[PDB]
Image (cartoon, rainbow over the protein chains, first blue to last red):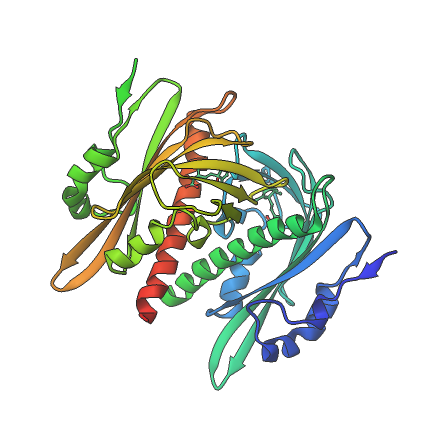
Length: 193
Length: 193
Ligand SMILES: CC1=CC(=O)CC(C)(C)[C@@]1(O)/C=C/C(C)=C\C(=O)O
Ligand SMILES: CC1=CC(=O)CC(C)(C)[C@@]1(O)/C=C/C(C)=C\C(=O)O
């Protein structure tokens, strides 16, 4: 029947084992899900050579996904938008023609622990039951500093598609956006200001 | 009625004016098209800190688009594939679910001038009449060497879509793949071998 994910029990690509062992409790706490037979889930990681708060300042901007995500034509939150759990955004995504619309809900926002997450709750695309969580972590070794971002999701496998294609699609989207996040924040860190 | 494109008469993003003035004859020769009212066309550029042949070795691999393009699940050319004008490839693209299929024809392959191009001639997506050309150019200044890649396309604007969304879609795809090309070839150049 239902199962618990195992992301917190194996090393995700692009993470070292030493890094994983430092993150294993966070992965258990924030990146575990109970999933049903029609669902899949994945955990992706991205190392970033920038301080945590530099990365978090970008990651946390629910109303400006275009700043670290590809193919965002627009994102609207409506005036009086205040960043609070339950707020929603309408994203127009130009990954194809016509452009897709995704309505997304802010699920988590913890500025102290550097955790956020959202759920897709409308739109005209095929990803159903999509929910993701992103956490940001600082590392240090001999005075050197870096960040690891972890992003996991759960989603329904769409009718007529395999889990492997579903995971390949969502994994590729998340991985490429994490690479943009790394570039944007490493540029920020390099240039200071 | 029909018009000639003007890419060879203005500076595309990410190119310096000095670079453009060196490339203007190539842009006129390889990146100009006669287009009809229902069509749009764009020219994109990418500077790469690697020698021309390092970039060209990758650009020229019609059967391995996955090496510098995002979201390629597979590409099949069939046994006895020989790289000749008229050869075709079946690309499966995982930019959405279900994955798209594009059947593409090799239009140009000039290893001396570093020119290639392809036309989409089948599949189950919406891009109709898509044709692109890619050229690769070497620059030198005071012993320093770099490459510029130019990629242009012509495509039909799909029913119910604006030219601006059509250009935004194709421009973003091409720009992001040119960035992967730059990363892949700059890594190659940095590591030599
Ligand atoms: C890029 C794209 C293409 C689709 O077909 C679905 C949807 C529009 C939701 C999406 O924005 C997917 C976004 C995902 C998976 C994650 C994110 O944004 O963190
Ligand atoms: C990424 C993608 C999404 C689509 O919806 C159309 C198609 C499948 C053709 C495509 O491969 C487009 C590829 C383009 C424009 C250029 C290329 O490859 O040089």
